[PDB]
Image (cartoon, chains in turn blue, yellow):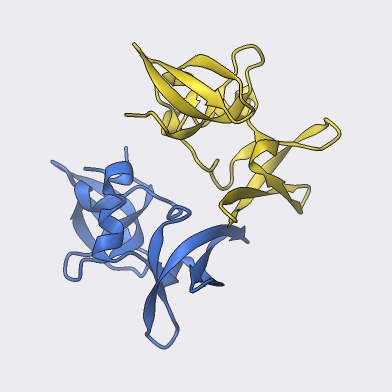
Length: 119
Length: 119
């Protein structure tokens, strides 16, 4: 089953995809999702991406601490003490981000559906 | 089609999996593979892993320049100038390896078949 898998899944209200885990197969193409911030909802498999981590060379949305965001390209992954970090490039400069600070816009996540979607 | 995809595929004679590209669908579950060292052969889809790069936390076989090899665990990926590098941990120490210096033993590659295999 897909239960227990870490995924990046669409939040319907805003169209962005966020890191989370599938917790239940709700049936008929629907899954219960526990997002890493603790929010839960049902999501269609077509809006769930099976990429842990988000792939190298993917355009993502990086989150700054003062609630700013920007596009960037994934140039590295690093594990440390069991936690995932992304190296993201913006204008030729790379910066590290924790897992929780990397999300996908509607357009960014849609690009990954054919290869990674559970549709 | 799977043609053009970078994969890690089994070399039948020795059981190890090596980086390469699918160049033809030979039919009936068989693919022509161009390995990164220039060798080509037909390989069964069940012996082809769709992981570019080989995943974080995977046990791999790292190649030293003087023809020694050892097991290690993938702890990072890095892109630089369009080339892929792996950070591999052995006894708590991490070392970088080019793509060509990371392969999978029979046992290491077999582990990845359920999630990544083209069988």
